[PDB]
Structures are given as structure tokens and as C-alpha cells.
Image (tube, rainbow, N blue to C red):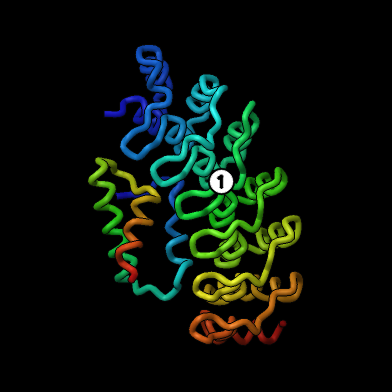
């Protein structure tokens, strides 16, 4: 779906620069899945931070 | 499921009046993400709904209303960019703690800067917002201003804000490292030439700021100017 207006995706990228596009896509796909469990059509920071927490290491 | 909240996302004013009139206890009800109606009206810049809701929240300190991610309506406001909404939320009886951090440890200033909202960032700083709160990755707003390559923000933070300039993040990067990794040659030299940024520090992989340059053109330009 789409990112909420106040979302900050360009925050996950600034951390340990050098993430393959694949990982970025996995994170986004994972965030979208989390929004779905909330019955929301928009992605919030929590979805992004959570998605990142389990796609990086 | 959360009618009022929905009305706020869609900016259905007449709808908000109606729902609140019927069940006043909905003003501060939190939805599935821990948000109250004000989080959403602010998120979608519904100026009328926001004012209306605030008129009913005179006793409220926004610091007591972080959503599930730790974001208060004020963090949301600073991230969206509208100076007028931020002002509205600020000029109330009780004032928001300008340094309140989210669960990732970020402040409102981190948010406005990363999105390049100059006016909002200037407003926070002019009212006392610290320019050195370190988030979970040990980055301060300057780390973000450099990565987006905003000269305007770098001077605001290092000038008016007297920001620290050589702090290194969890990755070992100072703001300079960020400017060069993203191809912002002029912001990089601005940090070195005007605000005394050191370019001899090395990150956790032994690299120096000039060694993480987007390409050896930015690299060349930088060295040719510091």
C-alpha cells in the first residue's frame, strides 16, 4: 500500500548504508504485511522499524 | 471500527462533531495503533478538525499521548511540515517537551530536518529544542541534514544551533561521512570549511569519510576543496 504522510523511510536507510535493493524490498513487503494485521491501508513508522528489525541482521 | 479516527483521516468535520456529540469519551480513545483522533487529523493536515479537537483538549499535555510507536501528535506535526499546525499545537496552556523521544529515540527536530522542513526546524530550535539528542543509532539531526545534503539545514544546525560536528554514529560515521556517501560534495566541504568538521576519523570498517564517497568525482571534488 502507501506510506503514511508522517512516515520516515529515509531513516532506515541512513543507518548502516549499503543495503541491497532486495533487502529494502523485503522490509517494505514486511511493513505492508504488518499494516494488514492492523487492517490499515497505510504504513506507519512502527511497521517500518519492525520490518527493519527482522531483515537486516 | 474507529469511526471518529476515520473521519479525521478523511477530514469529515461534520462527521467528527456528530460522533463526539454522541459519545464524548471518544475524544481520547486510542485506536489499534495507540493513536487518538488528534494523531490522524494532524497527520492529514485537517486544520478545522485539529482546531476543533484542540478546543476540547485544553487540559491535555501532548507528551502524555505517544502512539504505539512513541509518536505524539507533536512528532507527527513536525514530520508533516506545516508550520501553522506545529504553532497551533505549541501555543497552548501546557507546552510539549521539544526533546521528547520516540521509541527509536528520535526527536521532532530529527523528523523536520530529515524531511527538510526549514521553518519547522527553525521554530523548534528557536524555542529551545536541543540539536544534540542522540537516537538509537547515535545520530543527531545534523547526521540527517548531511545525508539529504541540505546546506540550508546544515547552517541552521551548526550556526544558530551550535551543533556538534564530529560525533560518530553506530556505524562510525560523522555527518561528513553521510554527505559524501550520498554525493553531496558541497555540503561536505561546507561542514569542513565553515564548521570545522574533521575528515581524518575512520569508521568501523577503517574507512575515512573520503573513502565512502558515492563516486570518485565527489571524492575528487571534496579533496580539491578542503
Q: Which residue is mark 1?
A: B100
The residue that appears at 58% across and 33% down in the rendered structure is: B89
Picture quarter with the C terminus of chain A: bottom left
Mark 1, chain letter? B
Residue A22 position, x and y percent, is 29, 71
Frontmost residue, B28 versus B53? B28
| Relative height, residue B47 to residue B184 (above, below) | above
The residue that appears at 47% across and 44% down in the rendered structure is: B71
Q: How many marks?
A: 1
Residue B133 position, x and y percent, is 60, 56
The residue that appears at 60% across and 47% down in the rendered structure is: B99
| Relative height, residue A11 to residue B217 (above, below) | above
Disc 1 is placed on an element classified as: loop
| Relative height, residue B118 to residue B189 (above, below) | above
- Mark 1: few, some, or many residues within 10 Å (few <14, many ≥20)? many
Residue B5 position, x and y percent, is 37, 29
The residue that appears at 24% across and 52% down in the rendered structure is: A33
Looking at the image, residue B184 sits to the left or right of residue B32; the answer is right
Looking at the image, residue B59 sits to the left or right of residue B195; the answer is left
Amino acid at each position: 500500500m502507501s506510506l503514511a504522510p508522517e512516515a520516515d523511510l529515509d531513516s532506515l536507510i541512513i543507518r548502516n548504508d549499503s543495503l541491497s535493493g532486495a533487502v529494502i524490498a523485503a522490509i517494505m513487503q514486511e511493513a505492508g504485511l504488518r499494516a494488514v494485521r492492523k487492517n490499515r491501508y497505510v504504513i506507519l513508522q512502527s511497521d517500518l522499524e519492525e520490518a527493519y528489525a527482522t531483515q537486516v541482521k | 471500527n474507529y469511526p471518529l479516527h476515520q473521519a479525521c483521516m478523511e477530514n469529515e468535520f461534520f462527521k467528527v462533531q456528530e460522533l463526539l456529540h454522541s459519545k464524548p469519551s471518544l475524544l481520547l480513545q486510542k485506536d489499534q495503533d495507540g493513536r487518538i483522533p488528534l494523531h490522524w487529523s494532524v497527520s492529514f493536515q485537517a486544520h478545522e478538525i485539529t482546531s476543533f479537537l484542540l478546543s476540547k483538549m485544553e487540559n491535555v499535555n501532548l507528551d502524555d499521548y505517544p502512539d504505539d510507536s512513541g509518536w505524539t501528535p507533536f512528532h507527527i506535526a513536525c514530520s508533516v511540515g506545516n508550520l501553522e499546525v506545529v504553532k497551533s499545537l505549541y501555543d497552548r496552556p501546557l507546552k510539549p517537551d521539544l526533546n521528547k523521544i520516540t521509541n527509536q529515540g528520535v526527536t521532532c527536530l530529527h523528523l523536520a530536518v530529515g524531511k527538510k522542513w526549514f521553518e519547522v526546524s527553525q521554530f523548534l530550535i528557536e524555542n529551545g529544542a536541543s540539536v544534540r539528542i542522540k537516537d538509537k543509532f547515535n545520530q543527531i539531526p545534523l547526521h540527517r541534514a548531511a545525508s539529504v545534503g541540505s546546506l540550508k539545514l546544515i547552517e541552521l544546525l551548526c550556526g544558530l544551533g551550535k551543533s556538534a560536528v564530529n560525533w560518530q554514529d553506530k556505524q562510525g560515521w560523522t555527518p561528513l561521512f553521510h554527505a559524501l556517501a550520498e554525493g553531496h560534495g558541497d555540503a561536505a566541504v561546507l561542514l569542513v570549511e565553515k564548521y570545522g568538521a574533521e575528515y581524518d576519523l575512520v569508521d568501523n570498517k577503517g574507512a575515512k569519510a573520503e573513502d565512502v564517497a558515492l563516486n570518485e568525482q565527489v571524492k575528487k571534488f571534496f579533496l580539491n576543496n578542503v
